[PDB]
View (tube, rainbow, N blue to C red):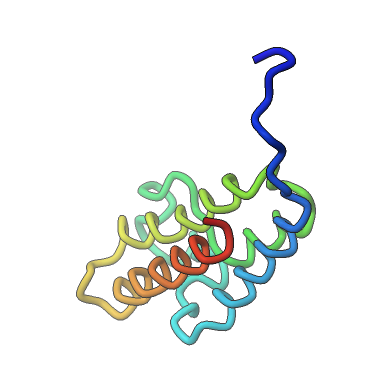
Length: 115
């Protein structure tokens, strides 16, 4: 409350460390469905169904331009990429499996880097 604060967690390295995580997600062999925005002209149903499209290149541009106020808003967009994938793709599909694998990969890096 006013003039009453928990001790200050060092967040000075968060930007660099989110960038490194994102590099590792970019270079994963199963990243290919997530590298670029879904083409809304060429994929019937995507625009209407997926209210907030998100992809790794869009996260990279947001990160690089100071559009993440803190490390939690960064994690929310990464998770959005996988929630969207689950919304639109069957589990038993190459893309569906890619999304589960990448979400797992992400959540471990996240816990190991920050928890």
